[PDB]
Image (cartoon, rainbow over all chains, first blue to last red; front, side, top):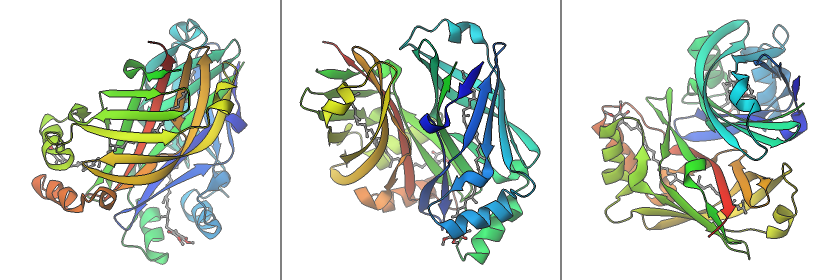
Length: 171
Length: 174
Ligand SMILES: COC1=C(OC)C(=O)C(C/C=C(\C)CC/C=C(\C)CC/C=C(\C)CC/C=C(\C)CC/C=C(\C)CC/C=C(\C)CC/C=C(\C)CCC=C(C)C)=C(C)C1=O
Ligand SMILES: COC1=C(OC)C(=O)C(C/C=C(\C)CC/C=C(\C)CC/C=C(\C)CC/C=C(\C)CC/C=C(\C)CC/C=C(\C)CC/C=C(\C)CCC=C(C)C)=C(C)C1=O
């Protein structure tokens, strides 16, 4: 019933390399749906990675995301829709929400800190109140991160990746 | 105007990275802020209100890094073009790039934030960072203090970069 409006939404993440160099990246194409029973799914087109350096995007698409095998990452959660449907337009609810992220067919559970705000009769916003930190090891990507750091000669790429999102859904 | 920040509805957070591979999210519990009708905006952070979930770490940050006894407030200052924001209908959003200045521990540094402004109702707006603002320790002459914290906590490394995010609600009220 609720569908994600990609043009209004943003999913970003921060990498830290060489100890002190933080950079923010994004994915350009998301999809998402929340059904009346509160089953929520967001799908990220991993090919739509955009880090600002095209050759880096390609290396990530080949080596880390492996998009030729896994063009989609999935984020899944189960909401209690009662309090969300009760929000008046303009009103917000803080949700601390278990969810699952699936990357390459590996899944891991995290706890998200989200803010849900009703925008109008048919539009809803969900934002990360604080970014959600994932770790390469959770998806068996440690050797893939280490591979990158090297061939594109760095001291190091941090194995933690904080993820933020502003998601707009429309009825 | 004037617009005032509703602390209970807002959150300013930041991420530190330790031992190369562990990112942790922390926040401040007490903010204030005002935007005047001319678009002059100021956010104050009470730095004593740091919350990392470890009291000892909170105390080290207060004393060593923030020096709350000399500087209990950090300030964020900007000048907004109010017209396009005020023109938003409830539920509508505008992306903007906002030059701003942060003053922390008696030093200042300028940034440009990528923000989304959304009108919530006739007297309330939400402002969120679409990407965090990345502060570096050297921006505020804090490098040695970061290394001191690293040393105190027995860490092999603390990143000198700190991405800062916010979800801020402002209300046209007294
Ligand atoms: C070519 O030149 C090069 C360089 O420079 C020249 C380089 O520096 C480098 C070095 C590499 C760089 C420094 C960058 C490296 C970046 C790294 C390695 C990649 C990290 C990627 C990770 C696997 C993370 C990817 C992100 C995920 C796919 C997204 C997951 C999203 C999750 C966490 C959820 C977030 C959203 C929220 C929780 C909202 C959810 C809410 C819904 C589910 C429900 C909503 C419903 C409502 C109503 C409540 C290279 C390699 C290079 O080639
Ligand atoms: C025993 O316990 C301990 C540990 O546990 C193991 C430790 O790991 C450790 C080791 C320490 C580490 C783990 C942590 C490292 C911490 C380090 C030093 C980080 C330090 C943090 C600071 C330097 C960063 C501070 C950032 C802030 C002050 C800046 C805030 C700026 C904000 C976000 C500005 C953005 C907002 C604006 C752009 C909005 C403008 C307003 C308008 C747009 C509003 C518009 C109005 C309309 C009308 C709506 C210790 C010490 C310990 O004691």
